[PDB]
Image: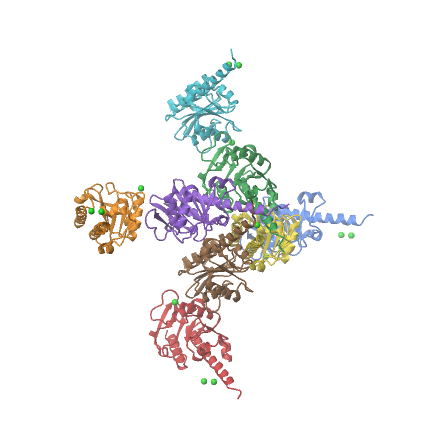
Chain colours: A blue, B yellow, C brown, D red, E purple, F green, G orange, H cyan
Amino acid sequence: RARLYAAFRQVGEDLFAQGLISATAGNFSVRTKGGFLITKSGVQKARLTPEDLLEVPLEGPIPEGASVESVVHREVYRRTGARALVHAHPRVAVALSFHLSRLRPLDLEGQHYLKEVPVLAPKTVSATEEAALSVAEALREHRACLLRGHGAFAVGLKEAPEEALLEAYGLMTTLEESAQILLYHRLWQGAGPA
Amino acid sequence: RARLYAAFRQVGEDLFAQGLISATAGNFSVRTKGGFLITKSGVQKARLTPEDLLEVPLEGPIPEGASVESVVHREVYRRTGARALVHAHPRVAVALSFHLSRLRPLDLEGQHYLKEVPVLAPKTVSATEEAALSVAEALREHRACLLRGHGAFAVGLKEAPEEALLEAYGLMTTLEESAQILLYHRLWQGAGPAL
Amino acid sequence: RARLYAAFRQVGEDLFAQGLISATAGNFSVRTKGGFLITKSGVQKARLTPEDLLEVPLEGPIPEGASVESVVHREVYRRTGARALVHAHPRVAVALSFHLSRLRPLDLEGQHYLKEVPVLAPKTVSATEEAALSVAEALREHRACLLRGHGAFAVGLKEAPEEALLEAYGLMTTLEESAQILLYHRLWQGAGPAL
Amino acid sequence: RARLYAAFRQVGEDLFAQGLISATAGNFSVRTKGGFLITKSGVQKARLTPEDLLEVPLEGPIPEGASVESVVHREVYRRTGARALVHAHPRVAVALSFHLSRLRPLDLEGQHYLKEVPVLAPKTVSATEEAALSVAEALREHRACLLRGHGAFAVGLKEAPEEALLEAYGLMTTLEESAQILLYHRLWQGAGPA
Amino acid sequence: RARLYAAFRQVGEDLFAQGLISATAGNFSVRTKGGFLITKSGVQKARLTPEDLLEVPLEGPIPEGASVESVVHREVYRRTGARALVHAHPRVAVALSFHLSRLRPLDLEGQHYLKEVPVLAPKTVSATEEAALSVAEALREHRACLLRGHGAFAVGLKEAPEEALLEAYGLMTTLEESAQILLYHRLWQGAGPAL
Amino acid sequence: RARLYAAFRQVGEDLFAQGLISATAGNFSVRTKGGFLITKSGVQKARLTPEDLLEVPLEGPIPEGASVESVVHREVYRRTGARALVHAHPRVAVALSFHLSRLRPLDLEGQHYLKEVPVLAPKTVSATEEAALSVAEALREHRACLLRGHGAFAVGLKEAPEEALLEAYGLMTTLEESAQILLYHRLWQGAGPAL
Amino acid sequence: RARLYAAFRQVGEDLFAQGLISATAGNFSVRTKGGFLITKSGVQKARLTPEDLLEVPLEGPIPEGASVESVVHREVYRRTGARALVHAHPRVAVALSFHLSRLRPLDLEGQHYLKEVPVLAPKTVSATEEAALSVAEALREHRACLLRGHGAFAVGLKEAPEEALLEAYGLMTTLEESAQILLYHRLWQGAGPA
Amino acid sequence: RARLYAAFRQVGEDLFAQGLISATAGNFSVRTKGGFLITKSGVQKARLTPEDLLEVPLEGPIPEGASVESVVHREVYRRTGARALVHAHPRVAVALSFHLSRLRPLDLEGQHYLKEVPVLAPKTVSATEEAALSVAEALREHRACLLRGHGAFAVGLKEAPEEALLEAYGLMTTLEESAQILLYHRLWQGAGPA
Ligand SMILES: [Cl-]
Ligand SMILES: [Cl-]
Ligand SMILES: [Cl-]
Ligand SMILES: [Cl-]
Ligand SMILES: [Cl-]
Ligand SMILES: [Cl-]
Ligand SMILES: [Cl-]
Ligand SMILES: [Cl-]
Ligand SMILES: [Cl-]
Ligand SMILES: [Cl-]
Ligand SMILES: [Cl-]
Ligand SMILES: [Cl-]
Ligand SMILES: [Cl-]
């Protein structure tokens, strides 16, 4: 438990530090024996405490106080073999999500780890079964996905929960980095010839 | 769920019994909060089991194993207020589809529930966005439509999914009954005068 | 009650199986001490349940939920000695109804049980006192009648309600069989000579 | 029990006094835990004794000695939420029943409490399942109803049986009063101009 | 007994399902040591119960409640070696009976099992010794026959009563299938040429 | 075994219900390691029991009691890669078989699954090596074929025997549906113009 | 038992004395609680002993030694309310059976007790289910019946077995007497005018 | 057991001595209470020991070490009333099997005991359910059968296992003898006239 809480605390701290989340935006979880452990709603992710996490069953009503995206996390664990999930709001990737149907990284790291990131535009993108189903089906075949104008989800598959969470965290940072590289590459080209 | 499963099971059994479908022909679905629930590809609809149905999102990858016509169902739900959809192969209606641009029932039930059934004749009519787009646009203004040489689609609009499905099923049976009445009416007339 | 329910259940299952009704088409009733017991509106007759039937008085408000044709059944019971009534939609008979003023069976069974089936063509034929009055007056002299483009009504006269209902059901099946025989007889003749 | 018997005695006395019943005509009841308590057949309603009342179940054979209209009362309790029922023979209302399909009061009291009174003309109007079904269905939507050439039924809905009975009694007196007002209004008009 | 009852039950269910009988139309029997076992009058053959069958002697009073066609069955057993008899009302075959003096199948199954089906046109065709005698004499040389405008009779000859009944039932279904094939063949030809 | 038996049972029940077979008409089989499993002669296919099936080797004596068409099934398995075979008697398709040298579906399902159905007209068509050889050679290039005046054969190719059988069954139903559509299309056209 | 045996002995003695049976021809029985008691096969009916009678159940194999017509008696008890049955061979009635489809007595006794006697001609007339069914159905509506060229059956309906047997015996003697009267009447007429 | 082993040893010795088998070719068995006792795979049949035999059930997996043709023997016992089975490789009969669809002996012994020997040519002729079904169905109507290019099977029907085995052995030797006679008869004729 101590180490696992540490992984959550670390991911929250690093996501905030890199500008992938701020304030209360974003949420993350890991698959547990009973279901999944997720961050509570409205808490400061960059400064998490053990009491800021709650276990949610894959079946039944969602405990009050859980992240509003719990319905989405639950569906992903139900339909995929995900071991951890990170939801964040990569700014550049989100901006690019209005312009692309899929994000294809130009860089090696992104091509290797993400391959291609689909951009989903369901009527509702947050805290709905609609959003949940769309995200869950996309992550059945992709490690990450973008919700147009909202944010992104990244999946961890490693056996150890702490490692799966750090894995999902890494994919999320790789996504924003790939989005930034795509933007810089395009702006440089657009500013030429020169 | 059990009740909704029952509705799918019953619709499949009844369509089969009435000769509107056989083997793995046809498919049906209902709108859900997540998107829509539809019959899987290649299953015997007259003998459906819960595992024979799957949910498909309106946005995102269409799950593997879903009905080959899922693209059409999805588009109908995207563009219309349909709460349920039934795709079947009413034999007489399909035969008449080669000869009409629209089917206008002679019987009261058909005139009341269907009014007029347009016949669409796109390049492709199955698993294609051609059919998908044409069918969806058509169902925005009509409760049912015919795809020349393929089959027909009927929509249910009631709030309860099971009721919407039964409503769609009812329109499909009304369609084939109206087509048969049209055929019988024409053949009787064609075989006369007979004093 | 169970036995009478059984009769309603069986009549619905058999009419459906024979293609005389589908979905929520048609309705049937039996005369009771209080008035009459009839199928509710919008139920699947091929799969009736006891809660799907309700009693209606000959005098007073027609209970909500009762068959939309209850006005017609009520009038028939008011004006005739009918003990049971079946309203169905025999497809071939309905197709022929547009072409005949009366259907005269060629087969012995039809000539014996039906004799002659008048075709009524009122402005309205469903849930209307038009149909109600015409149908009731017609059934005062005939065991069955056809409503042009809508369907047909057949009456049962036996004392036991379940037997009256089965009798009515039998006349309805005899009617569609006689209509089909008429059609087949005409089409065979029309396709000849063929030496 | 004492108070309830008092309500029955009072209603019988007041109905007789006002000429709504005489001799053995009429009958009344209240819904009870076991079914309903009704006046026995052929007794003098204006001078009831506790032994003149009997409880009848909503299911099964009707106890011998019960009012001949018990079958009607039973059906009303079965099909409606009636808590009490009064059957009487308002003379003017009955006379008007041959001429109207429905009685619509001109007076405020009648319009407010009765609204409109349907006139029913089933083949049989007394002690039959036919009469019972007709009356029961009418009282599902109306507080009172007239049986052409026979009499009228009025329903009480209050929780307390004594109060429901006094309520049904009041509606019955309101019906005859409204019928009398309709008659007087018509006769005055018919006798003019003058 | 149970097994024989089963055969009667199954024959009734299958004839009904195939549209060869409905309500109380038709009847069937098997030869027994005492005479023959036949369906009672007015029962729903598609839903037979053991109490719905009764034994009739070849000589003596025909028990009350026995099928109205018992006179015909009795005569067939008296004059032929029939081990079972099925009387049904194949609709297309009956329609063709008004137009043919004999029905000659075009299909192999029909040519093999039926060969030729004579059409009898007596003054009376039901419950009459007219029909009784004509039918019996006809079945002495043919496995099945048609009574113009009434129905048809098919005989079973196997030793086991249940097998004889199933054999008779099979010939009856073969007869209507052959009649339908004849009709379809003629209508297709009649609607041409169509280049 | 139970599952495979189920598939045979279901195929028989469904073919019967759809009017493609009746009594003891038709037969079906699946390829096995030893040769093939087929329905016995004279059994009611709509009501099959495990004891109603028997295995036949491709080389050696055909067991007594095996379907009379076993010679044909055997030859098909010998000469083709068929994994299952269904022989039925689709009435409209058989009627059309007298008029066509090949049946070409107008409907999409038929064009996709059948493409073209050749009509074979050998001297003999049942239990004969004539039919056996012609049918087998035909099924080497087509998924189904018609034997003029007899019936039709449809092949299943999937690896799982139960799936191959259901596939064959599906092609058989598609064949009769395509034949009916052809007939209806022609009769409607033939009865016109009708302004 | 003693009295009942007496009835059997008496009927056998009187049937023989009157020439309705001789030797071992004929047989008779009475309905018993367990089934029926019938004469054994091949015994001298005119000189019966208690050991010459055996009880047969209405269900199951027929005891060996029972009359060959037991199958017929059994069917009659099964299908009719017969309480006793007598099978005999009235000579004149049998002779007339070749010429008539039914025997209608000219005499009062015969018309009253027999009314009309049907003549049955099933392929087999003795010891077969065929004969049994024919006889049983005829006796459902008639008190006696003739089997062409074989003999006749007569039914007793009285409650007491001894009385039912004497009743069947009386009907049998009435049948032969009526047949004799019919013959004498015809011969006298045929020999005239004179 | 001793005597039965003796029968197996003897049959192996005599089959080898007469050239019907050599090395490890061939196999034989007898029906037992539990199933059948057959020679193990790859053993020297001409020099069998009790440990060279194993019992195989008619149901379930085939014990490892059993003859590769056990599947065939099993099917024969399942489908026929065979009490013993001998599989051998009669050289002349095998040579003739490429030329005939059936072997019909010219000699009395062969005609009497074999009558006619069908030649089977299934795609696979050894250790397959295909071979098993073909052989089993042929032996339902014949005492022996030839598998084109492979060898032959002969059935014993006697009650005693030892006798049934010696019976199958005799039929096998009769088959090769009949094949040799057919060959010699043909060669003599072909070498003439002379
Ligand atoms: Cl939601
Ligand atoms: Cl910038
Ligand atoms: Cl820029
Ligand atoms: Cl036509
Ligand atoms: Cl009553
Ligand atoms: Cl006054
Ligand atoms: Cl006045
Ligand atoms: Cl017998
Ligand atoms: Cl004399
Ligand atoms: Cl004389
Ligand atoms: Cl294998
Ligand atoms: Cl040599
Ligand atoms: Cl040589």
The answer to whether one can see residue A28 in this image is: no
**Residue D88: which quarter of the image?**
bottom left
Choose between G106 and E40: the one closer to the eye.
Answer: G106
- Number of numbered labels in the structure image: 0
Left or right side of A70 for D120: left
- Is D53 left or right of C128, judged from the image as shown? left
The residue positioned farthest toward the right in the image shown: A194
**Farthest top residue?**
H194
Camera sees residue F107: yes
Q: Quadrant of the C terminus of chain B?
A: bottom right
Indicate left or right for G52 with C83 as reference.
left
- The residue sitting at 50% across, 86% down in the picture is D191
> In the rendered view, would you say D90 is above or below H178?
below
Q: Residue furthest bottom?
A: D194
Residue G40, image x, y percentages: 22, 43
Q: Position of residue H15 (x, y in %)?
A: 45, 19
**Place of residue C186 in the rendered image (x, y in percent of width and height, measured from the top left):** 54, 52
- Horizontal side of E60 relative to B34 (left or right) equals left
